[PDB]
Image 1 (tube, helix red, strand yellow):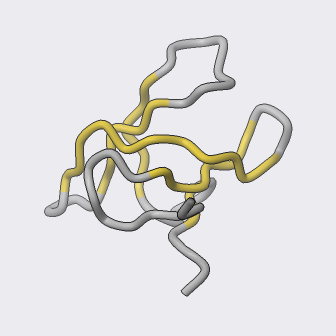
Image 2 (cartoon, rainbow, N blue to C red; image 1 turned 120 degrees about the vertical axis):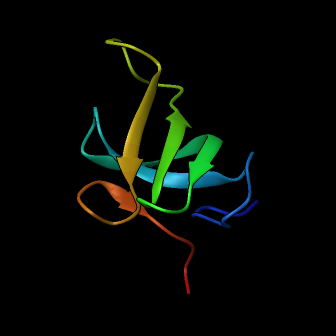
Length: 64
């Protein structure tokens, strides 16, 4: 039970949207160079996967 980017593939990060919530979304793949992750969302109607960057907008790492 780790709500946030644990930097591990398969970790459940917090993504914002849909409800404007930071909802536990799962990392499917990580790009470390650009610093993006292929995140798979549970509550997401358009697509289910997306490449977004950590805390660039709607992505939150772990508590700290």
